[PDB]
Image (tube, rainbow, N blue to C red; front, side, top):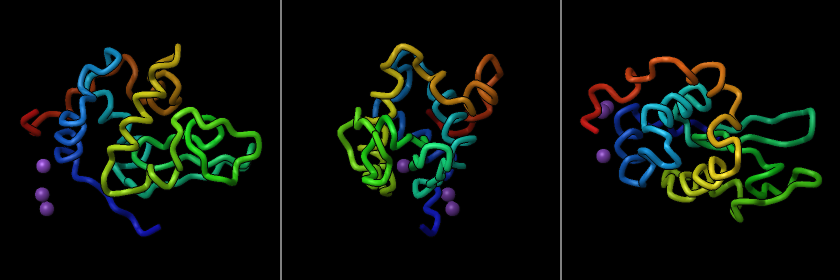
Length: 133
Ligand code: NA
Ligand code: NA
Ligand code: NA
């Protein structure tokens, strides 16, 4: 869909408001670094994985095969109990709640490869600097 992209500090603030800072021991800077490499802060971001017909959705690019139902991913399991479309709305409440569910599993935030490659073990302070959070 046409993009609906937050501004770095507005998302930082919203995520903070929604209880993301420190959630599961994950700092806001880390959630910001994730959203950045994942969707570029684009809440409408979708990405089709031709390998298993799955698609990644919204800000956190959550996968339809395990987390949200998109009604088009064969053999999917809906762990968040949400429609993937719910993860593509300007209001990121449902999205944040699913992201929380995702990092509650054993691998936490390491479930996202991009986070592992871009954010993990690296200085991420740049992501929240200036935001007043
Ligand atoms: Na602005
Ligand atoms: Na502006
Ligand atoms: Na605001």
